[PDB]
Length: 148
Ligand SMILES: CSc1scc2c1-c1nc(SCC(=O)C(C)(C)C)ncc1CC2
Image 1 (cartoon, rainbow, N blue to C red):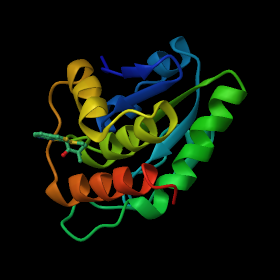
Image 2: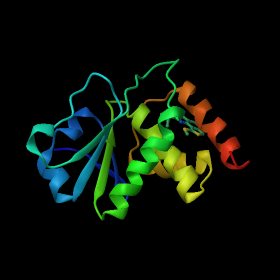
Image 3: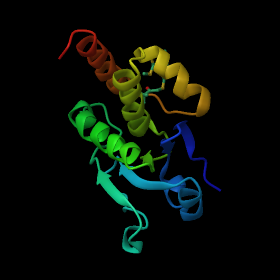
């Protein structure tokens, strides 16, 4: 039903149609959800199962995602520390969600921007591009290899 592309054993990437698959989320022991949109609903919120973080962003040329980098990392860390998986998603392009996942890999695995990009690409091949987001990731790499 839902490709919940597993980036790491505790970190899953998907689109809106993927976040609407409760069985899959429970099969994979997901307890945390990051919704990187403004307008989509927090699926299954009324069910009392998951914890959530909305990152209110749009697939745009002007959207800043680096602001939400530290937030998303602290949630990823709570899910792992608490031994449960996290699904970060947005919509069809997974452009917004994939930017954040990559950002995580570059900081917490210390990959390069491109090395993480080859890593994510290989697992989920279809990923709408966004040159605005790529620039922020490169800005992030500079800042990680500098200590800032
Ligand atoms: C960190 S992405 C990266 S790094 C080096 C290259 C690329 C790339 N990416 C994409 S789509 C993925 C995206 O744009 C994001 C939503 C994750 C920002 N198409 C083509 C290329 C060519 C070469």
